[PDB]
Amino acid sequence: GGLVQPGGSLRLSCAASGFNVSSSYIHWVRQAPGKGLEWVASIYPYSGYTSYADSVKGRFTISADTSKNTAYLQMNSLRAEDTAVYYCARKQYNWPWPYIHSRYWGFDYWGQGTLVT
Amino acid sequence: ITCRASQSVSSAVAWYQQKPGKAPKLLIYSASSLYSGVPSDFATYYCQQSYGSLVTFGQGTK
Amino acid sequence: VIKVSKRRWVVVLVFSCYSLCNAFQWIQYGSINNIFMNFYGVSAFAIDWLSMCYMLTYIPLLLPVAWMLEKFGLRTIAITGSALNCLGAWVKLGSLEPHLFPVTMVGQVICSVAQVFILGMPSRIASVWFGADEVSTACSVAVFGNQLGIAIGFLVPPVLVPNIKDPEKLAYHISIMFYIIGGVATFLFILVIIVFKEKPKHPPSRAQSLSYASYLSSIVRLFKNLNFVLLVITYGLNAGAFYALSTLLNRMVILHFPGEEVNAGRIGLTIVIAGMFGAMISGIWLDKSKTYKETTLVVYIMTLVGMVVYTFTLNLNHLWVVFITAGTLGFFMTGYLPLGFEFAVELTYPESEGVSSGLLNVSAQVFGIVFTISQGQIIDNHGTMFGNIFLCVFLALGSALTAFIKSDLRRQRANKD
Ligand SMILES: C[N+](C)(C)CCO
């Protein structure tokens, strides 16, 4: 976290411990003052699969070095819309147990947030 | 509270309790599974789907 | 009392069905090769080994299963093959997470073991249950089951599993395929336990009534034959070229026509189903013409031509030429298989069919491994054109040797005196 000038490039770096980051999915959720929680991107850091919200589109890019247990969200083009506390969340892989269990994990290990203005 | 979905999410909805100035807390996963760490005060409660390549929270409820 | 039952057609239709189910598993992964490589994050070599484990297991375990088919009898082998099919199909369920490619491989090695018990049965099922005017129909049904399993394992996986990237929506689509084939395998295993009988109450055939009232030694007199060694090597080159082309078909078709995974499975089906007409036509023409070396030579050279056509038109960006050329190549590659087996029976008449067939199989499997590994390295480095010219140069070599196999027909020399 920290302060950036519009049109800049910030690299948020989330670090985990106690669970290996390649086992799970890692999500980034921003929450601006008075707009509630808003999902940004996710990554399965073993398959490198990443997903992004149509809101960011091109600017943001999520990645992870699954050898130090850290994920990174780098920004490229910023607005006044992109200012908010950025939380790091984990979903654990939802195993395909059709009907018999069918358990849809929800982030259970949220991040303590980091402010970016 | 009532959370409805524009598509089929198929019980991949979770509920989160966010009290002011803090990271949220998971309450119910799978739409019907109480999370052990935070089992059931007053705060903002957000529902959230996980069915789809993009994860979508709710409007927000105080 | 000599009489044929009606269980003779149940026993075979059940065998043919679990025989079909194992063959789908042989290719269930090779058919979506780029999708499993993405799921498990492994190479193409690693997903190729899910096809090559069937070839590798068959080689050491061919003699032990022959010894157990003679010592324990037909029903134990049936129960064993169908149970190992069920067990592999049901172990594959515990590998549905990107990190669990060792578990998919363990389940596939179990299914490969099941293969060795399934492939030794057809001729003995025919012998034990069917009259002497029905044994060839029975063996044809029993081998048609396996090959229809290969054609269904090429067409169904891509249809059931899309080329998507999310590791947990893709495991949903893989788990549905694993569940179907674990449910089908379990149904056929339960069927076998109830349906399979060791023997019919009466002998079906006069030869079977007679038989009721050593392999290693055969193997060492078969390598005293230069013509049979030529035929072993050339049949191996041809059937191993087919194993290589099947394992590696998704790779090359997807390198050229990206996004066409459904049509890659359809082209595999085209290969196999055209080849079933090849085997049917060849077998008929051979049985009615008795020209063993000349038919073998013509269908081998035509295998060469069809690979040269397939090689040098795969880059024309027309996916319909790939259908023509693969359905032709399969026609002749699978049409050559009955010829090879028959000409080996003839070139070695006093010897046991089942040893000549076991040796022809062992060579096909050794060359299938050699080619699949080799070609995949060539393709990964030099492209599909050079990976395919690699398989044209061995079909040309095999064609050159098929010309040097002397037409020594010892079965026609004996059976009409
Ligand atoms: C006989 N199959 C082709 C099914 C397996 C090859 O190893």
Image: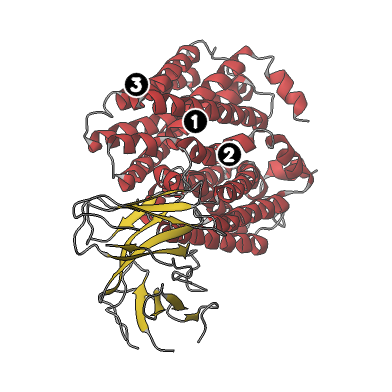
Residue appearing at x 33%, y 46% in the figure: C261
Instruction: Say which mark, if any, is on residue C305.
Output: 3
Which sits earlier in the primary sequence, circle 3 or circle 2?
Answer: 2
Both on one chain, marks 3 and 2?
A: yes
Identify the residue at the far front of this view.
A3
Sort mark 1 into few (<14), some (14-19) or many (20+) by Cα contacts within 10 Å. many
Residue receiving disc 1:
C337
Tag 2 subunit: C
Residue appearing at x 41%, y 72% in the figure: B23
Residue receiving disc 2:
C53
Three-letter amino acid code at disc 1? Leu
**Mark 3 → mark 1, Cα distance in angstroms:** 17 Å
Identify the residue at the far top of this view.
C404
Looking at the rendered structure, the secondary structure element under dot 2 is helix
Front residue of A65/A84: it is A84
Task: Tell me, yes or no, whether the two marked residues, 3 and 2, touch with CB atoms within 8 Å.
Answer: no
